[PDB]
Image: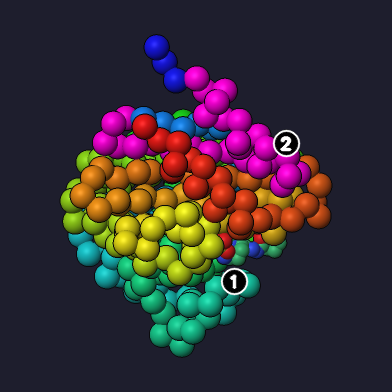
Amino acid sequence: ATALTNLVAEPFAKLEQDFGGSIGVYAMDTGSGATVSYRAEERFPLCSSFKGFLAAAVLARSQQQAGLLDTPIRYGKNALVPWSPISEKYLTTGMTVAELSAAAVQYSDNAAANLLLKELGGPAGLTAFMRSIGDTTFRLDRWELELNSAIPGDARDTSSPRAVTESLQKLTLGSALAAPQRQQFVDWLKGNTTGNHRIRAAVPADWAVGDKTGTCGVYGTANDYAVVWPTGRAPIVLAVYTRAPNKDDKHSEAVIAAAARLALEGLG
Ligand SMILES: *C(=O)N1C[C@H](NOS(=O)(=O)O)CC[C@H]1C(=O)NNC(=O)[C@@H]1CCNC1
């Protein structure tokens, strides 16, 4: 017999009703193939969370272009947009592509993300990279800061929890990238500084986590995705996305952490 997905799903429905919105979750246990799934194929805004995949796209390009990660990007003052705390420090020198990538992933730096998008041929170039690894759901259409609008019913700048999880697995654990690039992506995710109150909060401190967060700041829209390495057994990949119908509906980190915990405890 197969899993009773109603019983797996029920606690997410209670959680999202207290939240006043929708919660989407997909988790995969790479040891057993077990999954947990709730609204996993619905679209949610990416917000900042695209920046993880952006860094992966940069790493893929570095496989065709030796030394890409070493290349300095020397930008002018109009690259600077708010929530760019790392790129704002280096206006007088520039930053390398590696530094920009680290900042985009680990501080969610907005200007760094735009600078890397430009290197890859814009939002369409990142979307094309995702299509190359078989993700037909992901779409990035706009740039920082407009991509955060999170308007209900807008398909722009969205993906699904399942597609995010599947793509994250391919890139971090599968062989979609060469091993050095794969480990770099993992190391950048592991060094994230913005995720302590989201998926990380549901994971024992003994276990390594790499993640990328997103917070659109409107329509209850926020998210996190992660790889979790429990000691001595197969890693877990998961994504938790939220949205809500009213512009002034609050996002909640506690709800993301709670949904992560329900997903992790429900596997296998
Ligand atoms: C990503 O979603 N953003 C970058 C910053 N870090 O948050 S997080 O670690 O990724 O969760 C800040 C949140 C957000 C972002 O860019 N916020 N800025 C806005 O969305 C602008 C104000 C309202 N619309 C544009």
In the image, which residues are magenta? Answer: 4-33
Q: Locate residue 198 relative to residue 192 in the image: left or right.
A: right
Can residue 56 be seen here? yes
Q: Amino acid at mark 2?
A: Gly
Q: Amino acid at mark 1?
A: Trp
Tell me which residue sits at (44%, 41%) in the image. Answer: 265
In the rendered image, residue 88, in percent from the top left (x then y), is placed at 53, 80
Mark 1 sits near ligand 1, with its Cβ under 8 Å away: yes
Q: Is residue 216 above or below residue 115?
A: above
Q: Quick one: SS at disc 2?
A: loop
Q: Nearer the viewer, residue 186 or 235?
A: 235
Q: Which mark is residue 83?
A: 1
Can residue 122 be seen here? no
Ligand 1 is found in the corner quadrant, namely: bottom right
Q: Nearer the viewer, residue 80 or 212?
A: 212
Q: How many marks?
A: 2
Asked if residue 62 is among those painted magenta in the image, a careful observer would answer: no
Q: Locate residue 183 relative to residue 89 in the image: left or right.
A: left
Neighbour class for label 1 at 10 Å: few (<14), some, many (≥20)? some
Q: Is residue 202 above or below residue 67?
A: above
Tell me which residue sits at (30%, 51%) in the image. Answer: 229
Asked if residue 19 is among those painted magenta in the image, a careful observer would answer: yes
In the rendered image, residue 268, in percent from the top left (x then y), is placed at 36, 32
Q: Is residue 155 above or below residue 187?
A: above
The structure's colour scheme is rainbow
Tell me which residue sits at (48%, 77%) in the image. Answer: 86
Disc 1 and disc 2: Cα gap in Å? 26 Å
Q: Which residue is mark 2?
A: 153
